[PDB]
Amino acid sequence: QDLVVTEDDCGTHEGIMMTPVIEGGDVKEPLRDRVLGRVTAEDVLKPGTADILVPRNTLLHEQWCDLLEENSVDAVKVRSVVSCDTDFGVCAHCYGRDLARGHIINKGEAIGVIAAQSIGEPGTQLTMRESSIQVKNK
Amino acid sequence: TVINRDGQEEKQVSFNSIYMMADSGARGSAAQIRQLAGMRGLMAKPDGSI
Amino acid sequence: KPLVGTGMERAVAVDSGVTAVAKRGGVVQYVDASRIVIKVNEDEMYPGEAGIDIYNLTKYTRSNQNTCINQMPCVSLGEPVERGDVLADGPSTDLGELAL
Amino acid sequence: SVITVGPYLRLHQCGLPKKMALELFKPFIYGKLELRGLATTIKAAKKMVEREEAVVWDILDEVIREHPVLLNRAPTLHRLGIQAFEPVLIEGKAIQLHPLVCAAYNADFDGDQMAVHVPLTLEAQLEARALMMSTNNILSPANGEPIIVPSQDVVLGLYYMTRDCVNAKGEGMVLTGPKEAERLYRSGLASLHARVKVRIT
Amino acid sequence: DIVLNPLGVPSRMNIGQILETHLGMAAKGIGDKINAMLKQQQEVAKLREF
Amino acid sequence: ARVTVQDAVEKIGNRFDLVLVAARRARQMQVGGKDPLVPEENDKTTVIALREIEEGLINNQILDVRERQEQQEQ
Amino acid sequence: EIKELLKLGDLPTSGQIRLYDGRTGEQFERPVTVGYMYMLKLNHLVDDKMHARSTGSYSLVTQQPLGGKAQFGGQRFGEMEVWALEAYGAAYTLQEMLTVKSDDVNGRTKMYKNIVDGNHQMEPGMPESFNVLLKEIRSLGINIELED
Amino acid sequence: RQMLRKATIVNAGSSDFLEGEQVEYSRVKIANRELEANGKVGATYSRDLLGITKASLATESFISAASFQETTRVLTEAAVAGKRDELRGLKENVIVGRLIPAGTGYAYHQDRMRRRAAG
Amino acid sequence: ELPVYQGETTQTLQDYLMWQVELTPFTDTDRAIATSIVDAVDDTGYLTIQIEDIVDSIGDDEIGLEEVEAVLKRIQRFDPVGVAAKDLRDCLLIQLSQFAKETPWLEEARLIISDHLDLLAN
Amino acid sequence: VTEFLKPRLVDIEQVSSTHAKVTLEPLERGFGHTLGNALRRILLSSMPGCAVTEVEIDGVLHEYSTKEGVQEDILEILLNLKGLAVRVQGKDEVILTLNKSGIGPVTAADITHDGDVEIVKPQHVICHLTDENASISMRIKVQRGRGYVPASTRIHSEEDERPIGRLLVDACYSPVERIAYNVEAARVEQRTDLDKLVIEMETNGTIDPEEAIRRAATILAEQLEAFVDLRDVEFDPILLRPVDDLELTVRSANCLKAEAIHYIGDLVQRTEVELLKTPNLGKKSLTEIKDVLASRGLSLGMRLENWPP
Amino acid sequence: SVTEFLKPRLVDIEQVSSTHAKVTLEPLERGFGHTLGNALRRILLSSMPGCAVTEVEIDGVLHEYSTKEGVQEDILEILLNLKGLAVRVQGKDEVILTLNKSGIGPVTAADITHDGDVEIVKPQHVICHLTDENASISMRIKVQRGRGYVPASTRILVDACYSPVERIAYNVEAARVEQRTDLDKLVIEMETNGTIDPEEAIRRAATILAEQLEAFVDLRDVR
């Protein structure tokens, strides 16, 4: 409950890698929603060397997402709030929006409530609970 | 569902009410329909066994 | 009364005790919205008795659930009632069958 | 109060009974009576309210017109639990709810009740109008996908409306676009018809 | 006199209520036939046979 | 009726400070002394203030200038 | 047997029949089943569930209203409702909900006076329950005071 | 992040061996001591994971702690500590009844802070 | 089922007379007078002391005797009209002035009450 | 607009006293369905009918009670009288007495005869008697109304109160009670192909079929007069007496005449601080004005919206 | 008192354009808005006098399928544009039109020869497409009278839409007069393809609906 947005700029270029998870049999989640409401790292790399697509201070409005879906990118670093902070509150760009609004998050919104409420909202999960390797495609 | 036609080669999607409710996604599912027409299945768990 | 039931409605309405069942009764002589009298046959009553049975119907008595209870006679005049038959219908009862 | 469903309401509106909208908005009615000169004192306003005069209902309809009210279900485990709407003077003893917002409230109207609160200050009204309206919470905060998605009836209706069996009445003909609504009511053509060419802009 | 939701029966498996409804319709058809035979003043034999 | 608050939000861009700006203007309109710049349509002071702010006229800067001018004139 | 009884009662075998709209007078395609059913009335009418109050009597401790219907009292505003309001940023709404509605006997009176006069102004004051808690804690060997 | 606090340090670096200082502080100290006077006062630390409930026990504002766990104990802990809360937690303000430092109240709190030194 | 059994704060014809004071518009000085006046009201309904007594108890020689009268002339048309009467007779005067002048013998009754109650006493 | 031939009503059929099989006439393609639908919803929603409105018995006191000597309850008597059919003449609000003694079931045939009162189905029973000395006497007031009116939405008709021993019953005012229609081909083939719908209808036996049809077509013809020519393209304060009677002692009247003071209310919408800005009046004059308006002006406190002439 | 009903007094119109119109009626009796709305919708859409093209005879194959011959427009699109053509005849039942425009620009509606009774409300309507350099064809079309709508299957190529109204809809809302609510209020939206004033269309539909019932009443209960 003690989380309040008090800083506008993060100040660091650190982050965490974001790649689509695969279980071998099928892909569980593509790289379209894990980076949807995310701000890219200091620099994104294309399949062709000496090329950049977006700078470090641009939010993805699903247009650059559709663009990346055409370029078939796989290695994209995403700035997070656990790796980057200002010793107080949460920086804006380092959190994205991912809410009922289309703009960026504004200073003062209670992140600490929407988070830890969206986690406990699904309170209807459940109660009280080989040798060879085949391939699917080429 | 076969309907009258000169070629009678329709093989079109049926218009059953429960089937439409299931396919459209309004209410129900295949697991709920199979307990109404076919067999419900195992459906037994008095304890940690079957 | 329900157009489709199970048959146990009669037994439920009888064993509920909310209605007015008939005991050692014969020919009925007079009925009313609250009072009924029945003249028992000669071969049924014991000697030393007039041979009449009175029944007072419950009329608009407050219940424990803030509701109403009422009884009405099912016979009109000059009708014989055997032992074990119903005489009046209480709340949510129709002709001895439970009608909720 | 007991919550019910209403198909004629709007996404940003709610139906409140006239008896309940009179006890809650009592200070507002007193203020309006003292302003319009219909009640010379507070005692006169109270006596007019207790007697339920004819002008009292008109004044209540004038006052409750643009005053938001926040309604919420008792079991709430997310942010979409509390949302504000605009009152609508409807008879009866049941608060009417919008059908699309039910998914946010997780209600089926099988007997559940509803809680209602009336803001007083201007800032509370601004916070309810700019941050607590259903027209602002269309998407889910936990996902971002639209949570205002229709219910079972609307989906089934839209699914059955766009179909075609084999060659039902009104098949193979060419026509305009929005003009196709005339043939439906006039029985000139069925809503289910394949191979139909229409002008679409 | 009463209108319900047809979306309930698929998920909430209550075919029993629909069977009860069909049986009540049959019983009301029979009752309407008996009432017609009583209002049209037929003999006691026809009513007894029916 | 400002059914949806989107124009004034775009004009402010904070979503939180818009409530604070429209609060004092609506309070001034309710207490008196100020006339609505936009033509009223039988609405309340809050709706009129919000619709005037959505028109790009009233914001957090114009009100301060007006208050300073009123203080200097008196 | 149901089908046989339907056939005997001059009724369709399936149970469906054509119906007409009471507003447009048009035949309904896909005929719907018709029939009678045994309905029950429950004891959950709105004659007693409906409640409404703007002001009334308060309790002697912390000056808070009641919860029942007789002697009109407010409902339970649990933590799950205010936690939702924290996610909206409505600081003034929560303040007027927790200060000038239950506690702050002078605050709610000033609120009532301003609503009657049309000023629509509030004050935070001080919750009576906080003072009750302070008085209950000071009864033990704990010293708490308000410095400035 | 809410559970990645309460780290421990190994070096003194002009600071006592507290073994549990808050990561925030464990950085701010450095940010105030390294570039200002001497960087050699920098002390390496290891971010240790703490239980989601145990982290709650690290709440310094006892007023916003009694409502989360056993009251009496915490109360006594504060008493023997003789500490102050200064009303730095949202729940705290709520118990007091003023505007929360979040949302529409954020700006308000900001002004309050502007009234600390300047006024 | 805690400390207070239930606990309820009854209103009463003192708190109800205080309620009205707030709603009504007086100045900061008129408000005090009125507070003082309603303190003097008893269960029966009569200002207990006196007119000039309130003026002498307010300790300020400035405030006129009519000042209190002015306030006291408006407090006694509050809820039950005729509250805070002055010696079981001004009640009638206040209560009568209230309803309309279309009543049949208002003149006569006013004249009776004004100076002719001693005679009615017998 | 080529021909548009009207439907001349002919061949009215009356099978029984309740059911009817009135046919309509020869009409244009498409008019039959819409005409049947427009005539069905009007004949059922808006139709005058004479139904039992009030019953008053001497012996009984309230509904939830019983009378010694009868079989059915008093509440059932009202439920049986609620479905009585009667056609009243030109005059309205007819009241008739009903008295009977014996052991036979009291029917509708043993009702005191009146000139304007007619009964169509006297073969229904109202109550039952089980004692020779039992006698019943009551009165019934019957009125005419457009449609169903409950007792809780009529109970307000009385100006203040109703004498003990007077109970109200629900009113139906819908004597039709069953109406349907069906369309088929037309009898005459020489002319351009047409249709012919028949309005089948079972009433309660109060109003004639042809009268209801004509009256059910005259309501839909007069209501369509607004769609034939589209055109079109008080609250005051009680206190309004003048400044007189306020007993202006010396200078109050002069100050009111010099300041252009209005009748009453303009002095009430003023502040005591701004009153001192007026010409010299004095604290004594201010207190006198306050004491005077303490009975009529109410402490000179009010915020009015506007002032009409 | 039992034969008197309520009449709509708020008959204000709030049309936007010359074709689109929305007429609102606040005061109405309960259970009467739907009846009148459906009656008007069924009368004005299935029985209404008007003019429309019934058949076309263009030079080429008698079948509907034909080539472009430099027009570059499909033969199905040419027949569709002739369906939505507002033609009005003054005092004749059937009439013929013939025109052959040189292939230099877009074929507008003003290319039809002006007759004594043939009138067009919009001469800028699109009829054909621009040819390549020299392609030109003769129209040789004809129009007749009729009511309602007639498809191509029942009667004869281009569908004859005699109904002038393009779209019609009605909605019912709740309203109160002084005390009682739920009284239905009707709002009728309508769009007509010119040549007829929307309000005049409603007036003519109401007069047609009323003139078919004056004989069934025979001056009974009239005031």
Image: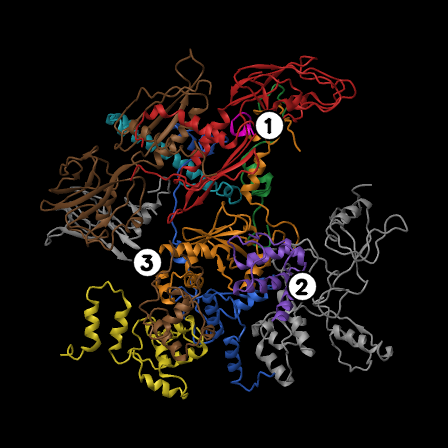
Chain colours: B green, D orange, E cyan, F purple, G blue, I yellow, J brown, K red
For residue A78, side relative to residue B6 (left or right): right
Residue J150: horizontal and vertical position, in percent? 31, 46
Residue D193: numbered disc: 1
- Distance, label 3 to label 2, CA atoms, is 65 Å
**Circle 2 or circle 1, nearest the eye:** 2
Label 3: which residue? C66
Q: Distance between the Cα atoms at labels 2 and 1?
A: 61 Å
Q: Mark 3, mark 2: which one is toward the viewer? A: 2
Label 1: element kind: loop
Q: Amino acid at mark 2?
A: Gln
* Above or below: residue J181 compared with residue A79: above
Residue identifier under label 2: F61
Number of residues whose C-alpha sits closer than 10 Å to that of mark 3, classed few (under 14), some (14–19) or many (20 or more)? few
Is F70 located above or below residue K25 in the figure? below
Label 2 packing within 10 angstroms: few (<14), some (14-19), many (20+) = few
**Is D189 a magenta residue?**
yes
Per the rendered image, the range of residues in magenta is: D182-191
Q: Pick the quarter of the image with the N terminus of chain C.
A: top left
Residue J31, percent across and down? 43, 24
Q: Is residue I56 left or right of residue K151?
A: left
